[PDB]
Image (cartoon, rainbow over all chains, first blue to last red; front, side, top):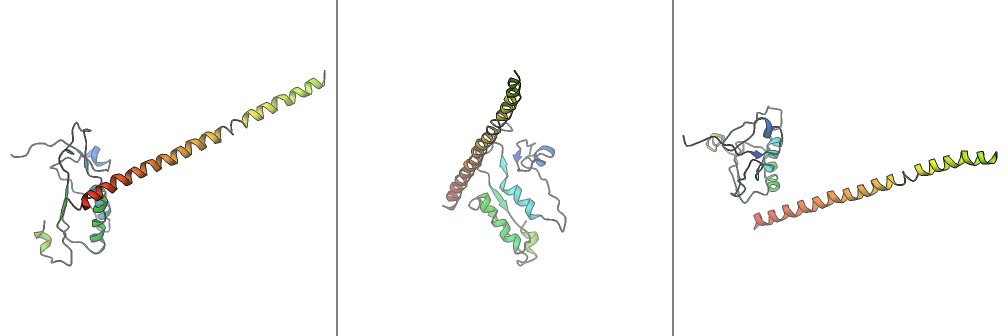
Amino acid sequence: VARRKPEQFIQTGISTIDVMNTLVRGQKLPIFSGSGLPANEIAAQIARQATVRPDLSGEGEKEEPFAVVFAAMGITQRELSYFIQEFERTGALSRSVLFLNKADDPTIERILTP
Amino acid sequence: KLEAILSQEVEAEIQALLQEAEAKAEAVKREAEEKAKALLQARERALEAQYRAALRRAESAG
C-alpha cells in the first residue's frame, strides 16, 4: 500500500535494457548467468555507468545524492580485487557500504549477510 | 596550316592532366587538414575526462 508505480528511468549504459525492459527505481531485474559463463565482467558495466537522467525523462534525481551498496556472498581471490578496482573507476568508496562475504569467511554467513 | 593541328592535340591533354593533378594536390591536402584537426579533437576530449575524474577522486579522498 505504501508503494506506487515508479516511472523515473536510469541510464545503465547498456542500450538493450533502457529500451526493452526499462530499468526504473524500486524494480528488480535479475541478470541470469550460467556456470562456465562470466558474471563479474557484465556486473561491473552496470556499476560505473549507473546514472539518472538529468531531464531526459522530464526530470532528474541528481539533485539528491545517488550512491550504491554492495554485498558479495561468496567470492574468490580474483573477484575480491576485481570489484574494488572498478569502484575506484566509479569514484565511489567514500559514499558506499560494502558487506563482502568471502568463501574463506564462514558458510553460514552466506544467508545471514543478505 | 598543318603545324597548327599538331599544337592542338597536345594543347588539351596538357591541361586535362594538369587540372587533374592540381585536384589530387588539393585533395590530399584537404584530408591532411581534416585529419590533424580530428587527432586533436580526440586529444581535447581526453584531457577533459582526466580532469573531471581527477577532481572527483580528490573530493572523495579528502
